[PDB]
Image 1 (cartoon, rainbow over the protein chains, first blue to last red):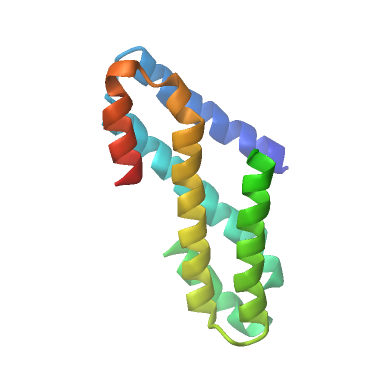
Image 2: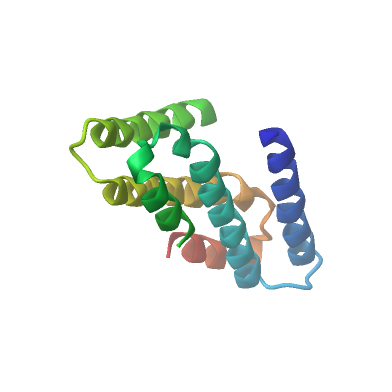
Length: 68
Length: 68
């Protein structure tokens, strides 16, 4: 599950690192793409893991804050 | 090394989750603190791991973009 999530994001990181090392994208473009990727990982871990210990009356507030 | 980094951040996450579940902090305050924590983890992984495959002429540009 999480390892399959990790593998998909590492394959995406590698796609951007390869474009960078191949000289098709700039270092700035590459760093911004990695940050976008890591931000999606952060939001997804909060929704799939941290959410489990949130009190039921706060579940709606938590989901909107995490996604927005 | 990385496991000692992981343990320190998990102890910080637990501090905020405990304050939340104890009712001392709001769900919003807790989510914003977790996001700050995860953002520092993202920036630190880019500087300690991704940096290793950056071309030497881009190392200065990479460090400033990651930190700023």
